[PDB]
Length: 192
Image (cartoon, rainbow, N blue to C red; front, side):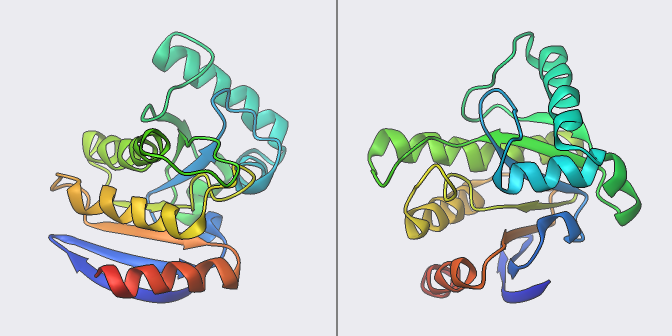
């Protein structure tokens, strides 16, 4: 874990970090999931496997939590399913917050932006609701969903700036790859 940027946004200490989100010191980590919470690849897989020892197992656990919480087997952008972090709890990570961003395939529009915005904002609001004081998120939609990396980080920062909460004191945005992190750094530097 390398911290690349740290800024004060209101009462929130916001950090940009490069590393493995399943090792970030936060109370809740966010999973960039699909609507059905099938954690078959990407950071969704790494989180699923790190929590349960088997990604398929966490998928099942996630679908069950989703049914209980939303009464159906999918979520919409902005809805956040909460699962126990299990094997990560020893590291101080209590929860995984599952969020779903839009599929972009290199496209960008106001409707896609709004969907991505809800996907970042939902988990912050979920943390505030639960009184969860620190949260880490990944680059939602910037994986196989193909959203432009700079648009993703810009949208994330809008959600952080507009978020109204007092319980949330610490927010981190975590990128796995050095390149991805350095692009976020450019956005962070000009926007804060």
